Image (cartoon, rainbow, N blue to C red; front, side, top):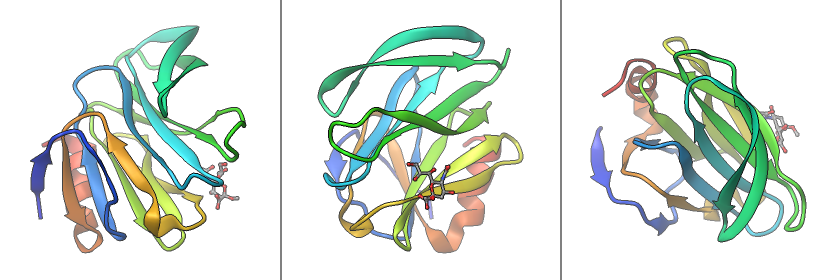
Length: 161
Ligand SMILES: CO[C@]1(C(=O)O)C[C@H](O)[C@@H](NC(C)=O)[C@H]([C@H](O)[C@H](O)CO)O1
């Protein structure tokens, strides 16, 4: 089950495996693209942030994104997604988190990520052309968990390692 931790790297994860990410600092957690119609990055925002514009390096280039975190005590993982190379990023499906863990999976034509509020998370997805060949760059330590053991992954997301 808990295969890792692996150090930050760019690689092509197998389909139907959760990549469980364990960031320590606010910032970009993971990014992945098919180079055609999906660029996804996950940003971790600290507790308690009134609307402000921040700079992030996404896919090698500096981007300005206006972020907020309404929670006083919980972190906020936000997916930013653009659907063409020169498109703008929009924000989707936050996870409010105490344990500071996130996960992403390639499955059935889509990229799945966790969502909602710990300790009662759900999942959400994004349709992604050529989903199986999406390369991911992790910016923090990560673990690999098969989809068959999703219930273990969900437990870690909800309650921590
Ligand atoms: C086209 O419908 C879908 C999709 O991709 O299958 C449905 C899906 O529930 C939705 N996911 C979320 C978290 O909103 C997703 C995004 O809106 C879109 O991919 C972002 O560009 O759109």
